Image (cartoon, rainbow, N blue to C red; front, side):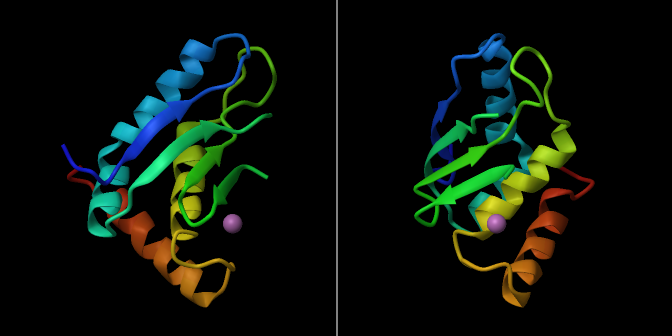
Length: 118
Ligand code: NI
C-alpha cells in the first residue's frame, strides 16, 4: 500500500471508543481521502479523535485531529461533514491561513475526493 496515509490512529477514552476507532479507520481507508493523499504526497503520522473547533492540523500534518462526537456517550457527527473537515485539515498541510489559495486547494481536493468512480 501507499506511504501516503495516516500511520497511526488514536481515539479517546469514552463509551463506544471501538465505534470511534472504526470511524477513523473508515476515513483513513476512504477512497477519496486516499486519492488526495496520493496525489498531494501526504503522509500524516497521527490521526486522532479530538476531545468533544471541529478539527486541528498540528505542524503541517504531523498530527490531525477530528471531532467525531456530538456528546460523550454514543452521538457521532455525520460522515460527510467529518470527511469535509478532514479535507480542510489536510489543506492546512500547505496553507496556514483560510485565504484564497487555501480555499482553491480545498475545492480541488473536495472534487477529487468526491469523484463518482471511487
Ligand atoms: Ni482551519
